[PDB]
Image 1 (cartoon, one colour):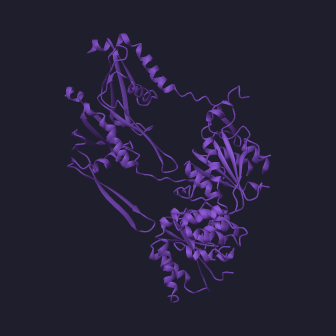
Image 2 (cartoon, rainbow over the protein chains, first blue to last red):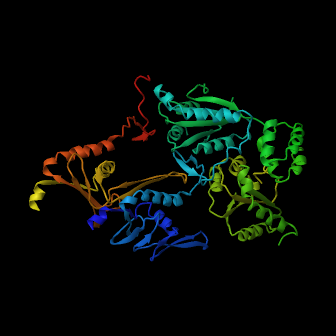
Image 3 (cartoon, each protein chain N blue to C red):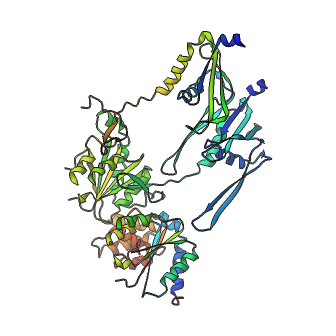
Length: 348
Length: 127
Length: 152
């Protein structure tokens, strides 16, 4: 017995670990094995209605099985404890024990990785939006997928003049640390309402997979909100032109702030704050340009270049406050039909 | 029981809006839609809304007309629901428009709106 | 048995002590040993998003192993209790028992120090900022590293 144990390995995964359900799920889908025993796991969702979504799946279950991974002949046992009870799931304490030779010990990580992979296909890719609830940030608006960077269409150079300033600010940790200055940066996206500011901020947060802790305009707790931001976040200050001003400046910089905090600021009309450490990158996103209209028309209708010019020279006339929200509205009502847009959008 | 064509002009608009997920996703626009059933009181509006919700087996999160929490109510709807706004002609207006669309809404939210006399809101993305 | 026990020492580290995870972490990275058994420890962080940062690491796990520290041939057992349950971590009560000769008893502190060292590489060096919350001081502004004296 001692000699065989030495020439063999074991691996105990106990029921507390998260890699217990993962491993059983993996071994259920393994093609070549022999698992004489089985245990049902039934998920069962009752909605607010009496309607039920239920699904059952069989798993190895208690007692030993066999498996052949890469020519290994792994022996697996699963055992339950007759005396101890876990309080996390209210079930007796279970344990899975894998056992192969010592020579193939390096397979276990591989195996777990495969299990992990069936576990890892989460791919949520989404941008949680926090919000203010008194002096504390609460989640708000169920984790919807982050908007694509292309979705936002602005002027020719502004898309790159900011996507590289931030990308520089993410690589200057040592430069900001050795000088003894705080590692923060502000931004002032300003322009007319409906120019695509918020869409760009959401696209950028999706680019850096951070979370927008939005805050729209109380001054004593404003500092607490600025200071207490979750991990991997991007602050947003809507309508900074509505103001407590001294407390605002104090909260922005006053030896009581957070360490790494990017803070964009949007205003509809930006008329001391422009000093570095405070707001230091100001750019004007405004109404639609003959480049913006062309890029929107080509985003909606792939191909079909001929109509594009016939639209642009048409929109050159009767244009006062032509904005991209208006183009978006007048482009969704004529979907999959540019010919209707040619006469509809031209008159508005 | 309503007029000859209105029963199909809406039962196919919604059925189109339930099949345009990719179209709304690739363009980068939110996946929502509003409706404005308007007419005299007692015309069978609410009956039609309930019949439609029964068709799609959703749940009517009814709300009749506070503005700071109106956004929270719009945002926090249960799964598989159809919002209903009774008497939208009784109004906070700027907060109403903000709650309807302001980069802080829900993802898939159909929202019918009924009024007894419907006299900026008519823009797409809104009604 | 009594004579060998007298000429040998033991050292019980029980699962309540903070020096339990430290010691297993140390013995995982020891180059020369023979640990036939293994136990997974999987850290698993779910952020506010569905995104997951997870990492698993193998440790000696229950049952006895061997190790050679400085020419000692230390024998180590790790055991679980079948009846008692700790409430601090919700797991059964575990215990690691080291056993060498009496002559090399002075190694244990050294060993634990090494383990402590892999534990001690914290080096946070930071200045928490308290603040007023009514008539009571609350932490405020996550423990950022203290600014260098030269900076001023």
